[PDB]
Image (cartoon, coloured by chain):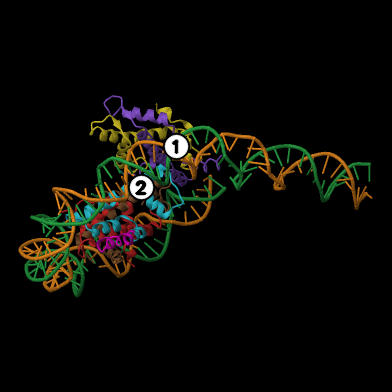
Chain colours: A yellow, B red, C purple, D brown, E cyan, F green, G orange
Amino acid sequence: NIQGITKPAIRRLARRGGVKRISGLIYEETRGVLKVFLENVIRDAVTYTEHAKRKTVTAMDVVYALKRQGRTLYGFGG
Amino acid sequence: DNIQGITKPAIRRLARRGGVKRISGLIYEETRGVLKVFLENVIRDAVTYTEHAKRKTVTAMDVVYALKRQGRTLYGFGG
Amino acid sequence: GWLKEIRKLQKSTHLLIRKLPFSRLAREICVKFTRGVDFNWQAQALLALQEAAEAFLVHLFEDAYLLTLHAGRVTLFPKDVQLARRIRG
Amino acid sequence: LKEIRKLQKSTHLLIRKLPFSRLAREICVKFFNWQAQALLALQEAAEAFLVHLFEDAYLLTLHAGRVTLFPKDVQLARRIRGL
Amino acid sequence: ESYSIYVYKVLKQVHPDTGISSKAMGIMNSFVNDIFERIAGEASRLAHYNKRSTITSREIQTAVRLLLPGELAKHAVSEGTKAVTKYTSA
DNA sequence: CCTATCCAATCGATGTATATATCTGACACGTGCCTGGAGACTAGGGAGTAATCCCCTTGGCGGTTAAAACGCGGGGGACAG
DNA sequence: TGTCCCCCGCGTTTTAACCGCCAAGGGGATTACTCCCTAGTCTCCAGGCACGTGTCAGATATATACATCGATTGGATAGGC
């Protein structure tokens, strides 16, 4: 399931960031960081929805978890 | 011109405390650069609190509140 | 396409990671912190995670390609992605 | 390599008080009365910011193989920090 | 309820010929309360430091002067110190 | 008649300008329900402000003393190839 | 590999940090009083909001237009001995 992040996907991601020669294990360095990041948002976001006795993380629970992480997402506020 | 009060041995101690083996030449001015642009963002954000109350004595509380606003809290000056 | 592919995705604005493997990875992470139970994920909540993670990854890559040229390199290395995760806190 | 293990084990202020006080009061008139506790609150955070910025810029130094600091070292560390 | 149409009429103020999608409105709908939480937030600390339990125009003014950058803070002060006058006198 | 000297002709690839309106489906807005916006009495507890205390930092003169500053030898580091 | 050179250490010199100590009122804080004006409550009253649809802002699909411009070799050709 961690190999769902494909090789031209990370290539396009680094191409958006402006990287000319994208390396090898870099592709394994990205999904690792993507495993570090996406955990740290989800560990907070279900913690918000478990206080209201709910089994569904909404967009606002993602916004609150990201505001806890230090970066404010705009275009998902309901 | 009080930017020369931050002297080359002081910047040398600041670099040797940070684990620098060999300091370059412009680092003895670059510090005088960044301490001119960091501290100013500490000064005005500490004087506006002084401009918020009716006072002219800028306490350490305004300083630690400005450093809280910038994002680096300071210990040892609350009460 | 060294001078061609650099000027296309930056002018473009849509997603780069596919939605369904990202959703599967987000669910596989979500079942860890829910004591092992299935969990409903809203369509806005998955796209929010996607838009956050894509922006975070391109920011981490554009903050590491400046470390690539610092060592006289044009080839990105994981030493730059582990150094960019050190001067951020 | 000699005094590196001397200041890291110590805790005293590297920058003197009165030049730092005059430097702070030069910015103060750009926008008063400064307590002696407020000058230490201005000096401790600035010194600990300078030492930490040099420590984080030295990681940019040993990334290119160099051991000597550079003007590009203090301009690349604050770029990732967003300051 | 939301700020959205209140954003739209001001959008009709600065740009009547220019249209908009619903995403860019929503970011706009996520913009104002992003700054509100700032300016009403900083003013929540400003009155607390001078032992005040009320917020006048001076607390919001000081929060604007402290949060917004130099050219933006002065421009919002000159846009803010005119609405406290035309509301009390008129 | 062998040879050096003007000519061009075939080989080929690599880019956007503004040319559109066509398969779907969402923004501007009309309408209407209403719940929040809004005028207004009323007690009252906070805002504003004078008098005074006394505090604490500005103000200043001196001692000797650790700390700042300056010039030379050179030796391993920075960067060029 | 390799040669250019930049701070490091040390001998020497000195100007200003720090301490010791008296001063003394700027003004922060405290007391107390008097009055703003804003929350509680209440009836009111009206832009702002969901329902719903008219249709226009836009986003591909993609045919192949668009004209020369960078370069190499074989055939005539005027002079030589």
**Picture quarter with the N terminus of chain A:** top left
Helix, strand or loop at disc 2? helix
Q: Is residue C29 visible?
A: yes
Which residues lie in the magenta part? E76-90
Q: Which mark is residue E77?
A: none
Q: CA distance from mark 1 to mark 2?
A: 28 Å
| Disc 2 target residue | E5
Q: Residue at x 23, y 33 (%)?
A: A52
| Disc 1 target residue | C15
Percent position of residue A49, x then y = 26, 33
Q: Read off the chain for label 2.
A: E
Q: Residue at x 40, y 48 (%)?
A: D67
Q: Does residue C84 appear left or right of residue F6 in this picture?
A: left
- Position of residue F79 relative to residue A37, above or below, is below
- Amino acid type, mark 1: Leu
Number of numbered discs visible in the structure rendering: 2
Residue B46, located in which quarter of the rendered image?
bottom left
Q: Residue A19: within the magenta?
A: no
Q: Look at discs 1 and 2 and give the one toward the viewer.
A: 2
Residue G34, located in which quarter of the rendered image?
bottom left
Q: Pick whichever, D1 or D7, lies toward us.
A: D7
Percent position of residue A60, x then y = 31, 38
